Length: 13
Length: 13
Length: 239
Ligand SMILES: O=C(O)CCc1cc(-c2ccccc2)n(-c2cccc(C(F)(F)F)c2)n1
Image (cartoon, rainbow over all chains, first blue to last red; front, top):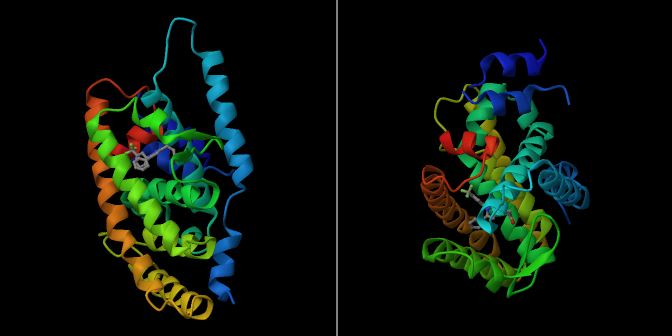
């Protein structure tokens, strides 16, 4: 599980 | 909660 | 005579010249980015410094003994509790070690006349800066050293006031152990000043108070439209 991809999914626009 | 804090902690350097 | 624990703490410390350079480079490369239209203020610049210093604090924390063993959810709760305290503690220690009275040693590694910052700032911020100054002075007169500094950083990070921790026991364990190591270090290294241990610990409530005031003020500034885009600082402020 790549951390960047999770951030991209989870962050506010 | 903070996607960013989470990312800064998880990312694999 | 430095306890083992404290040696483990010191090994976790960042390379200060490289951190200074990194932030400094970030700020230059930011003007490059920013259009020749959009301008930036002293307050704004200091917000960016705080933001970049936060990245460095999180990095320090994630690699540190004990903190590494926590689950990320616990790591987040600990950092959300203490980020502004760690900023203040880091600032204070720089003033003591690489600074002088009448001057502010910035995290980018230069000194500027206190006057030159204070003059830019209104009364609320001046008030905060003064209290910080007195802390610096108190800790200067205590002969605050790097071994003491690292202990206080761990005591701030591994706070007992943080609710809903999974592994609260590890956190209690770290508090107790760093506490005991600090007690040893002062009695072994400063044996004629038996007050030194107590004087160090009593700075922590003062740091906590100044940090809460800083946050309230910064949130005001943010809601006022005065804080330039600053993802991590404001994410922490929203915690
Ligand atoms: O030189 C530094 O260390 C970087 C900039 C800085 C200075 C302070 C500060 C603020 C009040 C008293 C003492 C130092 N910074 C700071 C510390 C805690 C909280 C905040 C906040 F709330 F504005 F985000 C800023 N950041």
